[PDB]
Image (cartoon, each protein chain N blue to C red):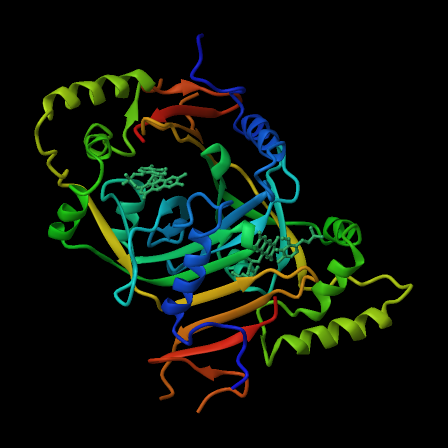
Amino acid sequence: FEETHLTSLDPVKQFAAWFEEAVQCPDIGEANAMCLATCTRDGKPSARMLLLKGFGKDGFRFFTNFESRKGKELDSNPFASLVFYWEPLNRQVRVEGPVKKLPEEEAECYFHSRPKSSQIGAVVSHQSSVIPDREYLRKKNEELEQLYQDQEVPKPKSWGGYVLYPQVMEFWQGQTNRLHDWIVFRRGLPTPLGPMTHRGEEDWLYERLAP
Amino acid sequence: FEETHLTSLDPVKQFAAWFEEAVQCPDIGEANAMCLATCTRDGKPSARMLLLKGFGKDGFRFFTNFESRKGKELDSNPFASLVFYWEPLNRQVRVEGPVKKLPEEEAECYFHSRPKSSQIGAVVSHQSSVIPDREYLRKKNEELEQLYQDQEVPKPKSWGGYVLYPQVMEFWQGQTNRLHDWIVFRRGLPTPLGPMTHRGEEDWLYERLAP
Ligand SMILES: Cc1cc2nc3c(=O)[nH]c(=O)nc-3n(C[C@H](O)[C@H](O)[C@H](O)COP(=O)(O)O)c2cc1C
Ligand SMILES: Cc1cc2nc3c(=O)[nH]c(=O)nc-3n(C[C@H](O)[C@H](O)[C@H](O)COP(=O)(O)O)c2cc1C
Ligand SMILES: Cc1ncc(COP(=O)(O)O)c(C=O)c1O
Ligand SMILES: Cc1ncc(COP(=O)(O)O)c(C=O)c1O
């Protein structure tokens, strides 16, 4: 089938190829940078930049302080959305799915893998809490350094990670002539579908949408 | 007051200075590019890249098709969030507030100001609708071109814009040493506040948060 213009009928394997091309682009510094959208049960959205830390069949992984705004929103409403935008390539990737907090064990393993300065940073910074000035931090940070000198920084109880499980993945490719390519993968049932709806690996269904 | 490190105690005037420095950066192509987060009344978030089209005291303006997913979510739940990320500067700006659809008249004025090709593009592209292949569009687009040759492209009824009214604005500045600067402006009452809470212009209140 002279196909669409994709590399894989697997949304995650497609993200991979696009992600690698981004990593290999000199003009993109943080290719794993993504904007995470979350909201309260009520319907009040929020969004902030984040770094994607590992991905695959299980989903997209990221870490934060469970007590940060995003944490308190994901825990009281396990639904999130991700947006990857790589301007140099004019590409955008959107991921929608339910979030599942990670196992404290894995978080721990990943935590101690970070640079000591990043670990210490996660302890002084009671993320999302109010403070007096930028020095307050420079100070605490300094103190905890001498404290944990030749020591293991314990992973804050409230520090961990989540993994988004891909329910909907979109691929956008800006074109010069404005007729942007746009394919949406979504997991449907009808194991019996639209004329323009096509079969993707697993229970994946894709189709092109008007830009 | 040897102040924080800002340019204005006005969140919008602060965004301005940061926005201008971005526009003047050779490494940032789309400085007005932002990720818009929205959700259903239920609490299901979504997010996609967008271009900021004008801003000020009234708020942040952007245009889309009212019948696109984002439209149907903003209309049934007038709350949105914006994220501006300028990696070359390691800066992030977050805007939270209620959305108000724009006057069809202004949309019209703005619509006809766009390049004809962009206007025609908004008519062939029944944004968010399913289609067969990329040619379907190349075709419609071509046909509407000869149609509107030496003619005014009417603004689609379902085409318009919204304006976010700044209820919460955040400024993030990544630092090398990881002790990122982060100030949050929010409109409060107590016209009588925290020790680390400071007065911003109007009914604006700001404070620094642990990164
Ligand atoms: C490029 C970039 C990457 C970031 N990565 C993370 C991250 O992995 N985890 C995190 O908690 N915050 C990260 N942040 C900071 C968040 O955007 C945010 O300021 C913080 O998590 C608090 O948001 P919240 O109050 O919505 O929870 C990053 C910021 C930038 C600009
Ligand atoms: C850099 C960039 C700028 C964009 N600007 C807009 C815009 O101003 N309005 C719009 O409707 N879509 C814009 N889009 C496309 C949206 O991200 C999205 O694909 C489209 O609006 C449909 O999203 P929705 O289905 O959530 O409504 C832009 C995409 C990129 C990558
Ligand atoms: C808020 C924040 N924390 C941490 C990091 C990087 O830390 P790590 O050593 O875990 O990759 C970044 C990188 O941009 C960041 O923006
Ligand atoms: C989806 C989309 N529409 C339109 C535009 C630009 O159109 P305009 O001439 O209104 O600035 C862009 C620019 O990136 C875009 O991504």
